[PDB]
Image (cartoon, rainbow, N blue to C red; front, side, top):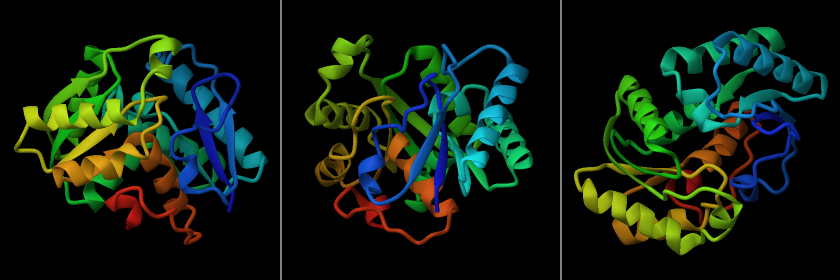
Length: 233
């Protein structure tokens, strides 16, 4: 079953982080050309998201995921829902979003006290914490990479992301689990290393997006093994 993904950039490229989980599966992307991942224009955003969902339906997608965490959480639960309802009505397909994916992953692992490890700015981390509070999770703290530009993003490796999660956890030792939400960075290998070092499960947002969209498409394909408890499943 073909999985459709709506993405932030104009070019319409399948996200790199998570694709490794499903090497045999067909993924098609359609680019919003947003200029932001946290845009102004409540109606305009819904409108472009609808337009792009319809483009994906015409290309044979069996489901559509809005594959951007920030865009789906920055205006809280009411907006994540509005996005989902608008896509499904315009397409007749089951639709979902990366923020729903994250919720779904955290629930599957039993997490309700969640430490945040992100690459976002303060205001954005605050909106994330607010979204998760609305969904009956307790955000217990946050540590962020605090980097910008391709150069610095390029310089991130697995170790950087593992250390990030350990930091976030040390700071919030009461946490049930960790949400790694590091848009644009490669996180898969970090997941089971963090779970080993800490004994607490990790959800990574982009990989959760792939997993959740693959679940929704209901084909039964399993993620490649070795990428943490959620995906070992």
